[PDB]
Image 1 (cartoon, rainbow, N blue to C red):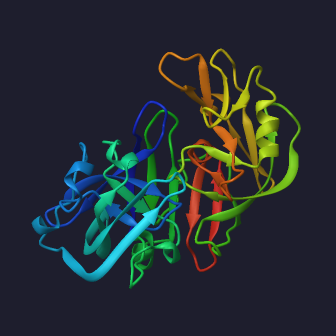
Image 2 (image 1 turned 180 degrees about the vertical axis):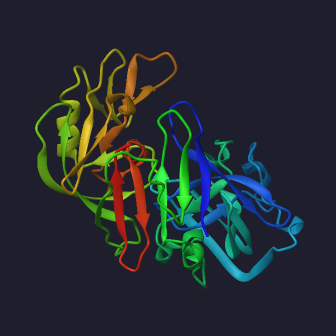
Length: 330
């Protein structure tokens, strides 16, 4: 089997991407944030505290003939940005882009933090990290990808995120028309539950490539590119007037600036992030100070190749017995 679904930016900055997901019988379609940095499939629901729902589409298990309470199971998750959610669990039929999993754990939110309530466009998350990070207790549950794996033509999914445009998540096949050149594969560590890999270095604009190992995670659920302070300083030093602002919470730059590209290494291959991808616009409406798309990972504890980086590539998440990551230009 295979699946193929379009993923669409939620706003004009590509702050996140939503992908339609069919849950239950008859189908209830919710727009979920596919997140390769977590491992819970959770939704706004009929059980979500009413004051914490503001425009989202909810899953109502009582209207699904295939929904079954997973008795005794609860979940609770906190994300790197400080947001959180918790609730109980149903199993139900879940389909993405024509690919169907029966008996998928669908985590029903009873509580969500402000950030989720305030984002009307995201109806929940679909985690695509390794199932060892799943928060369901007392019986940990499998991700949609893990459940689908044995039925897939190939045990892979791919992320092809657009810049200010829709893109595609495919399951079970590699679309050889979706990228240019060849795919370079690189080793993955699952020790922390993430798609964790080691970049071979970086360049700023047309500068020389610096060979250096950068351990980080491929995370579709994070907007920006978070790298070591040394690297990020070297980037923003090439932008006149750029500075790190403690009041704003990162690097800002004059909106009148032209940004240089940023290159990262995948083995001997190179992925180029155009400068425009690194512009996240005025810090506040009407401001001439713009927020940078490359930020320091210092104090996160991990480097994060988020959407800013991933949308510059066609990315293969290979969930074979020995997992790997592939990157191609496009």
